[PDB]
Length: 39
Ligand SMILES: [Zn+2]
Ligand SMILES: [Zn+2]
Image 1 (spheres, rainbow, N blue to C red):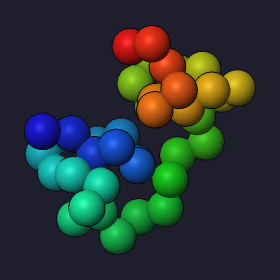
Image 2: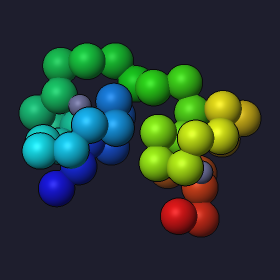
Image 3: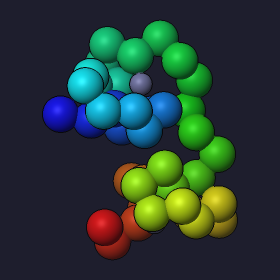
Image 4: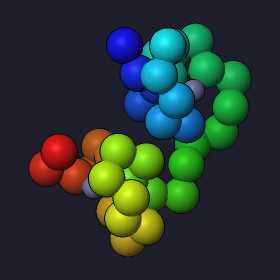
């Protein structure tokens, strides 16, 4: 259970009102996003 938008656990992007993160909230790259990242 983790937000695929802001990158905070305990919810889902479905539920999240917040706008997306810059890049990989998961791994930390700015160039790519979480959805892009192999991880
Ligand atoms: Zn969120
Ligand atoms: Zn990444």
